Length: 255
Ligand SMILES: NS(=O)(=O)c1ccc(CC(=O)NCC(=O)NO)cc1
Ligand SMILES: [Zn+2]
Image (cartoon, rainbow, N blue to C red; front, side, top):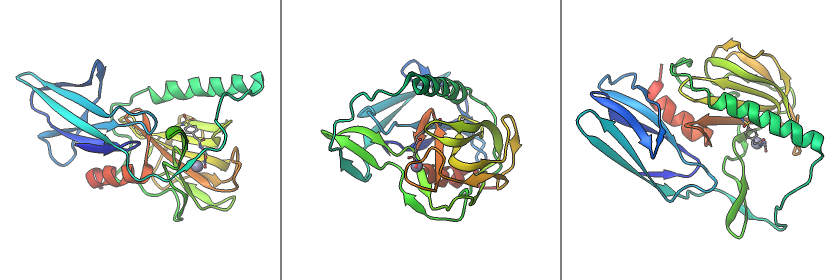
C-alpha cells in the first residue's frame, strides 16, 4: 500500500482467529469495524518528519501470519527554504521548565489508550469557516525538514465560537506555551482532537462533551500571526492531516 507522510490509514483485517498486530515489537491496538462484523480496524500513521521509507506490519493469527507492506509517499505539501539554519535557541529556564513540563503532561495523555469509542458518528468541522493555513506547510534547510504545521488553521476573528468536532472526554483545558489556550479531547482508540489559541475555554478537564457542543471561543493566544483556530488530530500516536483523517474516519463511522 502507499501512505503519504503525516497521514493516517485505517487498516481492515479479518477478525476470526486474530491475535495481534505489530510494527516490529510495538503493538498496535484494534477495534470493531462497525458495519462489517467479520472485520476489525487499526489506525496506522506515518510521521511527517523523518518517516521510514517503508513499513512492514504483521497481523498474527492462530493459524497464520499476514504481512502488510506500506510504502511511504511524500505527497504535495507546500514547502519553503529556510534562510537561517534553525539551530538551538536559548530560552530562559523559566520557559524551558514550562515547555518540558507541558510536554510530559501531553505525552502522558497521548499514551493513555482508551479502548472504546467515546465518539458519536462522524466528525464535523469545529466551525463553518475556511482554511487559512494548510496542514503540512513545511520549512526546510538542505531539503531536511526542520518544522511543519502540525494542524490546520481556520479563519476566525477573535471570539468566533468553537464546537467539539465529535463526542469525547476533555483531557486538557488550559493555557499552554506553544498552544495558547488549548483544548484536547479523547475520542477513544487513541484519537485526540485539538483546538488551540482560543480566547476563551468553556470546559473543564474530565468533562464528557457532545459533538457540536460549545468548547470555547477562537482567539490568538500563544499565536504570533493573529486571530485564528488551529485544529489538530492525533491518531495512531502521531499528529496527522485532520481533514484527510476526518474524511477517512467518517467514511467508516457515519451515524
Ligand atoms: N497536542 S500538543 O503535544 O500539546 C501540541 C501539538 C502541536 C503543536 C504545534 C503548534 O503549536 N502550532 C502552532 C501554530 O502555528 N498555529 O497556527 C503544539 C502542541
Ligand atoms: Zn496553526
